[PDB]
Image: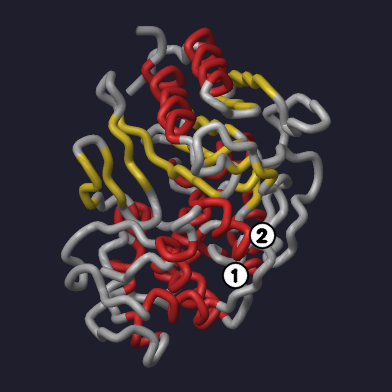
């Protein structure tokens, strides 16, 4: 159908509120069927004072899961992967249970324990512990495997980064290439995403970027600059770098059917219930807005960056919002409101 007009005054209010709650800077870009809405408030670097802008590059965190899912779904289109085959069929001896399938891994129904629960029990100390470390995919899987599974295979939704570390391992095993090459050839290049990179384990963000500021667990604590890290603890689960325009392009292309067959795009949208207003398909989230429309995309949290990248069912309207802080739930909940303003419009 047709959407209400985006509410720029509402978006402006959301950004201003995020700043009052602790975000150094916040921005949002809406690509509304060819008409751009772009707003930003605050600083990209709180020490030097440089203002944040919608062209600043940033770490997308978990949104990386959708890029991984797209590559895997293309491998299904090519006949190289079967979603219902066991993970152990492709990676022998990896998982303790042969019944855990690729589909379950992609929709977070595998029961694999999330190793980040151990890594980041304490926010800043955990970040300091892993920021300069380089892990192999096996290293992370092993960390997960020290714990038992949380549920029977396919039995329930339980978000776990381990699932997309397994995804990265699958892509590399099946294609014989690194995940960086696969993202480049299958997505970045075709869509011409010039602000999008996967540089793991490099710690530098190429070009003009917003710095990320990690909020400490203790109320009132000083912010920690968490911009430069290897993100090796996430890799195919969260190390992509992009911009508001590139993520809008990517989700619009995805929902309009340009990245895989119609059959695989329907598979990706087979929703597993997360809560009363959300669903998870295969590396894709569905959020149900107040005005009765659902949007599709992914959220991302990586140290110092909160990202919301969602598009309408047909991809005609896409929105990417970013606040350069993390471990601040107020900012997190506030930033979600950009979706309401951008898609539902003025109240």
Q: Are marks 2 and 1 in contact (CB under 8 Å)?
A: yes
The Cα atoms of the two marked residues, 2 and 1, are separated by: 8 Å
In the rendering, at what x and y percent does residue 292 appear?
25, 23
Name the spot of residue 306 as percent of width and height, x first: 53, 39
Q: Quadrant of residue 282?
A: bottom left
Q: Quadrant of the N terminus?
A: top left
The residue carrying pointer 1 sits among few (fewer than 14), some (14 to 19) or many (20 or more) residues within 10 Å by Cα, namely many
Residue 254 located left or right of residue 214: left
Q: Residue at x 45, y 33 (%)?
A: 332
Residue 29, quarter of picture? top right
| Residue denoted by label 2 | 198
Q: Position of residue 289 (x, y in %)?
A: 31, 26
Q: Residue at x 61, y 66 (%)?
A: 232
Q: Which residue is mark 1?
A: 179
**What kind of element bears circle 2?**
loop
Looking at the image, how many numbered discs can be counted on the residues? Answer: 2
Q: Residue at image x 74%, y 40%?
A: 209
């Amino acid at each position: 159908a047709d959407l209400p007009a985006p509410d720029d005054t509402g978006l402006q209010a959301v950004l201003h509120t995020a700043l009052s709650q602790g975000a150094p800077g916040a921005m949002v870009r809406v690509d509304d069927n060819g008409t751009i809405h772009q707003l930003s408030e605050g600083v990209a670097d709180r020490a030097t004072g440089r203002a944040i802008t919608t062209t600043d590059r940033f770490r997308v965190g978990s949104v990386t899961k959708s890029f991984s899912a797209v590559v895997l779904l293309q491998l299904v289109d090519e006949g190289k992967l079967d979603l219902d085959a066991s993970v152990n069929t492709y990676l022998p001896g990896l998982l303790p249970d042969d019944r855990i399938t690729v589909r379950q891994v992609m929709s977070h129904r595998s029961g694999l324990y999330d190793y980040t629960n151990d890594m980041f029990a304490q926010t800043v100390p955990g970040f300091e512990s892993v920021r300069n470390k380089v892990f192999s995919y096996q290293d992370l899987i092993t960390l997960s495997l020290k714990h038992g599974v949380t549920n029977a295979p396919g039995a329930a939704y339980s978000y776990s980064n381990t699932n997309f570390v397994v995804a990265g391992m699958l892509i590399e095993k099946l294609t014989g290439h690194s995940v960086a090459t696969e993202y480049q050839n299958r997505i970045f290049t075709p869509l011409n995403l010039t602000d999008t990179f996967y540089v793991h384990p490099d710690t530098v963000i190429p070009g003009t970027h917003a710095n990320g500021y990690l909020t400490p667990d203790e109320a009132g604590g000083a912010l920690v600059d968490s911009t430069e890290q290897t993100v090796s603890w996430a890799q195919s689960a969260g190390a992509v770098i992009s911009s508001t325009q590139d993520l809008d392009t990517f989700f619009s292309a995805l929902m309009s059917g340009q990245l895989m067959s119609a059959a695989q795009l329907a598979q990706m949208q087979q929703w597993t219930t997360v809560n009363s207003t959300q669903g998870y398909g295969l590396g894709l989230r569905r959020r149900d807005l107040s005005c009765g429309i659902s949007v599709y995309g992914h959220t991302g949290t990586v140290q110092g960056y909160y990202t919301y990248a969602f598009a309408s069912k047909d991809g005609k309207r896409s929105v990417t919002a970013l606040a350069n802080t993390s471990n601040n739930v107020n900012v997190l909940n506030t930033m979600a409101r950009t979706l309401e303003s951008a898609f539902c419009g003025k109240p």
